[PDB]
Amino acid sequence: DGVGSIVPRDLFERLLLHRNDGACPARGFYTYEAFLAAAAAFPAFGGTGNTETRKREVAAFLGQTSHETTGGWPTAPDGPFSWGYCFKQEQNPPSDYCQPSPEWPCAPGRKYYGRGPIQLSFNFNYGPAGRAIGVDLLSNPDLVATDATVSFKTALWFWMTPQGNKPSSHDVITGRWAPSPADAAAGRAPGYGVITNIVNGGLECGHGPDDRVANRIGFYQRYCGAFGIGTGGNLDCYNQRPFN
Image 1 (tube, rainbow, N blue to C red):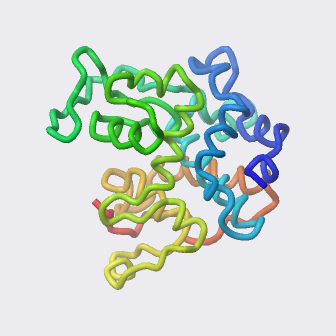
Image 2: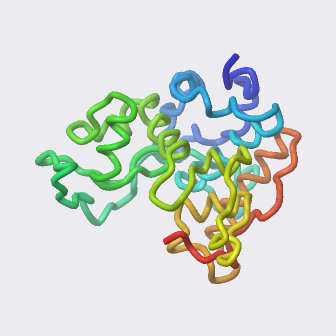
């Protein structure tokens, strides 16, 4: 009926084991209830494919957003891939990330640094994310760090929305995405690798083994293990030209 039927409370708490430790600034913020309320607004999320595919989408989603918010380190208790979701805002942002745009003006005094599970950044992403989900995030961007439902919603918005020449992460993981000829050329073949490419490929893909891509892969594998499902192939983007 919904995504709660494929990730019950005990799985979710064990997937995100340490998010609530005392060392995590976002602790107590990311609640199971917040997750479901967010998912209910994107019924296609976790509701597109057989049960396996559905579990995989939740693994992949959680794996990418875990990386963007990790508090892990190599000798972390239960490994570095149990420390997803430790942060909800960018540490030491060097900017207000306001790029004045006629389409999306900046609200005076409002900062658009990274917030939430996908580290939503820039007035020109807060704007569209706000419109998509019925909340004015251009004037009230701190809602991505103060309201956990909105927070997860922005992450899902990014996951479910295709941008320019990139498909949605959601269509890649559910198998809906068909590479172009210029994708095959550039090395981009369906799997978690293409999603790392969608998320931060300009920096991270196409130049061989990369510890940031490795950390994303690490979360995904553990999460798929917890789910009793395989990961699929092409886990990396080491030989993929970036979409960017």
